[PDB]
Image 1 (cartoon, rainbow, N blue to C red):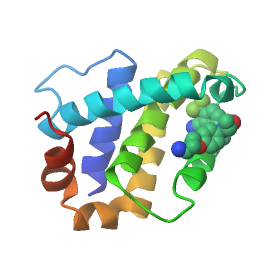
Image 2: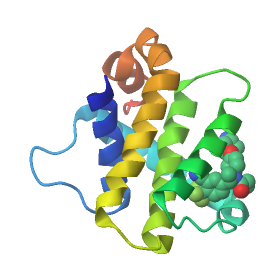
Image 3: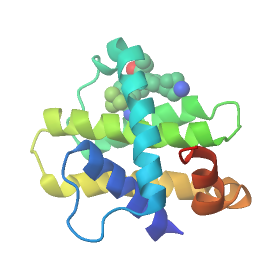
Amino acid sequence: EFGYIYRLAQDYLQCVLQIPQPGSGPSKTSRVLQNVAFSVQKEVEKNLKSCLDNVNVVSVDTARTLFNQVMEKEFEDGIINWGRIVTIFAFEGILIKKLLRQQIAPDVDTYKEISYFVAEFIMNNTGEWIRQNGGWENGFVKKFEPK
Ligand SMILES: *CCC(=O)N(c1ccc(O[C@@H]2CC[C@@H](N)C2)cc1)[C@@H](C)c1ccc(C(F)(F)F)c(C#N)c1
């Protein structure tokens, strides 16, 4: 459900921003996701450096527009797979790093807005495929957890 996906998206943004939230800590799914998505994010940052250096992410609306353009390109052939879902989180990590650095009126309460639209996209466009492929615990974690 939305709340579950929003918590994954929020946890990943907090991981990239170096602000882990105090308390019981991230779930097993979140821990596995942070590891795989961060690895994909680092690869994307290097491989698409010229492409990422040409944008100025001055606002949440600018980040939303950029994210939608990436999603149209990522899923243009209509196929969904777990590697593509991990790539969504990798792009939200890149967007929050650019927003911290380039946002016009830096607003600490706008990192949750990026997490929100990423969760809306995941739920609306990939949610049914995720559920049919086992959800996060029986699908995602089984595929990507350490061997
Ligand atoms: C380089 C083209 C470009 O400026 N661009 C863009 C980046 C990435 C894709 O598609 C991904 C790579 C190929 C597929 N696997 C998906 C498409 C277009 C823009 C729209 C862009 C630049 C920078 C960012 C950044 F992350 F830095 F904020 C985004 C985003 N989000 C998009």
